[PDB]
Image 1 (cartoon, rainbow, N blue to C red):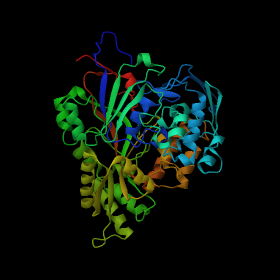
Image 2 (cartoon, helix red, strand yellow):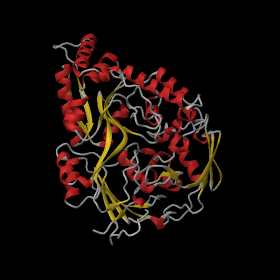
Image 3 (cartoon, rainbow, N blue to C red):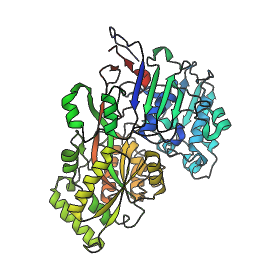
Image 4 (spheres, rainbow, N blue to C red):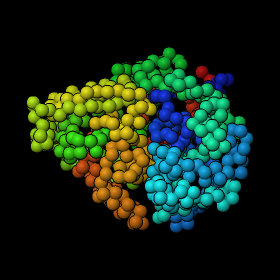
Length: 517
């Protein structure tokens, strides 16, 4: 943390943050969501980290170079250590990236190594080559060298993500799936795990071995798992919580902007809220059905009337303000809702559905006040505009994500946030073979457009290709885009160091501080 000259620090440097739900895991190779990553950034540090404004910056690597954007060499700082005092080395990175690639680990982010195009990853994921063939090596204890199969000028931007953080081999091998318990875990970020009570709290304490420990100010941070945005706001206003999670309740938000304006933080955020259709399950394998659902949803009602929190109606997967996005707004988005409704009714009528044999399906969402209220609104809208019936189903976060990977669903409430600011952070998740493809969308045309982006050495050709890949996704109605999120949350006046400038919202508690109050 960089405490401004003249700020008076509180005697007690503790923080309580709501984290939206109980985490899937604390193992960097078993996680894929925002709540998981929130805790992961305090505990495990990779090659690079985001600074307080989101810029990729030195993490365990103090400096790095690249040869033709294909061979990347990372110089690890000599004093990077784990919480047990042992050195973090390039061997840790070699083991960890191999463990991420290994199919036996079954990471949801195994494809992150495909997104960076590390040599031999496709064969490794497919079981054709052992994980030890991955294009990574330790040239010495403080030098990690990554070899890619093609030039990737933005490669280093990927490296702030939890999936490419180091994990301690000795703890993993000795304790298996209990390596992350407080008595066994070993961490290399600013914090260490103190307590973990499922569905109650995660408590982290400063890690004195952290190389940058002298600049850490907060001594203890607690992450809560509250999925009700109403309860989060209530426990923030009671004094328990210092920073809510960044999902705001429809019940209270308008009142909050009038009651505590300065605490309501609203900043750009590279995330898209959408309804994820399971493209492999009939009748959702029919484009007419998916297009009808996409067109009949009234984004103006949802975004401006039922939610009204500053979000922008969406017509694509990649947010249009992602660095490198130059998207073509489709003609259907400019039409009137009535015109979209008739086209939708027409397509479902064409698909075989009638008043006596209507389309009925499930709408799965993770337990939440906000998602439940939006799903009820969406159900009413679809009922009124298209005559379809939906059965709402809530599931807790960890179970919800497993369901989407299993494909045991029809339509699911979804949100994707960028992991690095470049359109492929979104687009790569729709590749046929992506470990993140919960839409179960498989388009050889889409795959080809993205493969072609690194075969050119020009930004304009790349942007044009991303635009066409989005048009392909749209023509197939792989998803139902709803809105581009804003990052809205409450933060107490005494929490310093939170700019809201990072569109990825990669917060590190090591950068915050509590002002005397």
